[PDB]
Amino acid sequence: SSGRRAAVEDNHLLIKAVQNEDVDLVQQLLEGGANVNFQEEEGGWTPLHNAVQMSREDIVELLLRHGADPVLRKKNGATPFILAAIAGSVKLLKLFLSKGADVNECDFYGFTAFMEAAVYGKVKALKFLYKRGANVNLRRKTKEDQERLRGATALMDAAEKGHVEVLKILLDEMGADVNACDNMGRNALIHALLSSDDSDVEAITHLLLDHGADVNVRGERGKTPLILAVEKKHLGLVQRLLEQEHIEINDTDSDGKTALLLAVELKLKKIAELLCKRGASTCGDLVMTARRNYDHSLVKVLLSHGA
Ligand SMILES: Nc1ncnc2c1ncn2[C@@H]1O[C@H](COP(=O)(O)O[C@@H]2[C@H](O)[C@@H](COP(=O)(O)O[C@@H]3[C@H](O)[C@@H](COP(=O)(O)O)O[C@H]3n3cnc4c(N)ncnc43)O[C@H]2n2cnc3c(N)ncnc32)[C@@H](O)[C@H]1O
């Protein structure tokens, strides 16, 4: 019982040794008899996981030769193979395939190597996984989710993190389905506009629209791409979104508000003016909203378009 406690320390040390990239210390601890397949209690991480996360092939090899299980999963269900995708290591993906990993295996949240590679903008890994049979259009199914016959896709992921290079490749080279929808009915376009990154959102939006993305999808709360473009207060997105010949300008959100109503509630002078060069002012309480806003430049615009 004093030995059971002392050893667990050696184990944690083996992990820490790996994290510190202390090759010699890892060799001592393993030769010393430390459990090479020890999993810490937090998230089920092993030395091998940590080694893969860090893209240290040499430490992976060492651990494997001391008998590390190459397909042992951590608590989230992710395997070392998957972790190597997040790391973008082709060498490690090639390796874990050779040791029994399935190219379309997934953690307990439906995440596949291919998906992780797109999330982390890992191009070479993406191309590798594709050419090794990765199912590009898989929709995330948690495990106790498949059993009940019941949703995001790699394309969506790349859209939310704003990886332009990856999005081009998925759409042009790998046959990604631009108009797939998750279980809340959001598509790659909606995800791009929901993300925290206004960084490359213009490119992602243009790209998606060229590849025939549906500008008229109902999101979380009736929120269309137009309404998100407006709520973002982005003139460029509203501008590009409106060059879509068949966009339901007057579509209404969850609250009944529309692209124009929200444009005016938010005092967007140019966006409201641009919308009015097509939008229906018959939401009605438009002018009354601009008046509550004390916005007489905007009250004038609304009336010229018959409110
Ligand atoms: N060396 C180590 N590195 C990192 N963590 C370590 C390390 N050593 C010990 N730990 C510790 O163990 C714990 C859990 O770590 P873990 O990563 O193994 O397990 C995570 C979590 O519990 C678990 C679930 O978290 P959640 O409740 O937030 O559930 C999340 C979400 O609701 C769900 C569905 O997403 P979606 O389909 O709706 O888009 O997956 C999460 N998720 C989001 N992006 C993911 C991704 N790219 N890949 C996998 N899962 C993702 O998944 C890990 N995880 C979460 N976000 C991640 C992300 N963005 N990229 C990679 N992995 C991610 C921790 O508590 C931690 O301290």
Image (spheres, grey):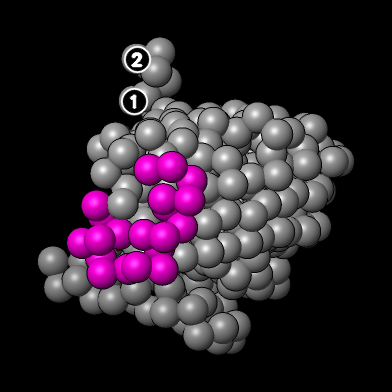
**Residue under circle 1?**
144
Whether residue 77 is visible, yes or no, is no
Residue 276, given in percent of the width and then of the height, sits at 52, 47
**Image quadrant of residue 139?**
top right
Is residue 304 inside the magenta stretch?
Answer: yes
Q: Quadrant of the N terminus?
A: bottom left
Q: Which mark is residue 125?
A: none
Crowdedness near tag 1: few (<14), some (14–19) or many (≥20) residues, C-alpha within 10 Å: few
**Three-letter amino acid code at disc 1?**
Glu
Please give left or right for residue 137 compared with residue 45 in the image: right
Residue at image point 34% right, 73% down: 12
Q: Is residue 148 left or right of residue 61?
A: left
Q: Going 84% across and 41% down the picture, which residue do you hit?
A: 172
> In the drawing, does residue 56 fall left or right of residue 186?
right
Identify the residue position indicated by label 2 in the image.
Answer: 148
Asked whether the beta carbons under mark 2 and mark 1 sit within 8 Å of each other, the answer is yes
Residue 11 is situated, as x and y percent measured from the top left of the image, at 36, 71
